[PDB]
Length: 302
Length: 14
Ligand SMILES: *[C@@H](O)c1ccccc1N
Ligand SMILES: [Ca+2]
Ligand SMILES: [Ca+2]
Ligand SMILES: [Cl-]
Ligand SMILES: [Cl-]
Ligand SMILES: [Cu+]
Ligand SMILES: [Mg+2]
Ligand SMILES: [Mg+2]
Ligand SMILES: [Mg+2]
Ligand SMILES: [Mg+2]
Image (cartoon, rainbow over all chains, first blue to last red; front, top):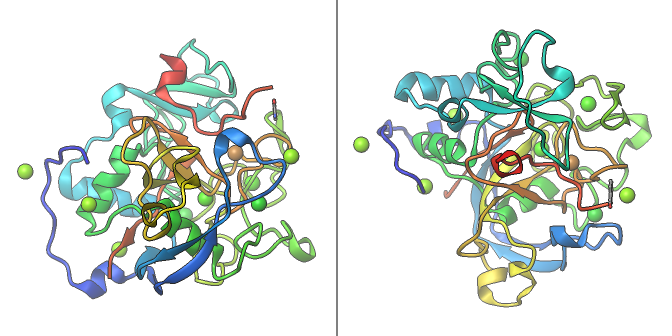
């Protein structure tokens, strides 16, 4: 937890819980066993995990909500402090300069000076037509800052995954095992040929409003696709392979690490590249980093 | 060829 220069407004439990669903205490099977999963992701093993009851946001935190936080606190995000953030190449306007540097493994990501949550494609862009889209260009530090100010916290990975699974046992996606059941789109991911052309068959070639598509069985929206969502846990591909109370009862993840867990996949994910919009999928990013496809939702103790 | 990258980090560019 970093240092914060704001204070926390007094709020009633009903105000905090608005927009949240109450997940009952219980067990669930976390993890996955897809043979094509990338070993370095540590999706396995599948294990029974017991969680205490918690609340979780039905929606990722929106631009309008993050703007309220910034209005109240003057909070300055990491992307503003560093002066740049990651934007998908095809979304940068031609007259907007970018840094000449490349992400070796993912050259479709460009570092854009001046890209941040209120200007998500760089200077000249805005969020005036996206108030109910998930806030992006928020680092893990920014996410924990908002959640703290909001009277909440980030979910653990296990809380995130229990809620995202929506009461189904070991299904592939939040809603079941078929990606487009009866040909209906259920999430905002990539269609077409990644990274060359997104056909937008699901309606969106960038972020969608936080209430797009149907909820899962617990009432959560866009747990799969739309934006990656920061979780509290440090990233490890093996800590959770241990079988102990620490890893199976309200697991908090490893005590140390270098990157924090992100869940759920994004509008950029595709079967032919990452296949990371399955509910067991997982990756990470370093806590000071920010990108146009990464946001968060909050959780809270009851 | 290597594990796909979905989360671009500042370190990838530094
Ligand atoms: C390399 O191994 C690679 C490259 C692109 C997509 C998937 C994989 N596994
Ligand atoms: Ca899409
Ligand atoms: Ca998501
Ligand atoms: Cl909107
Ligand atoms: Cl799976
Ligand atoms: Cu992905
Ligand atoms: Mg103070
Ligand atoms: Mg609220
Ligand atoms: Mg806290
Ligand atoms: Mg595959």
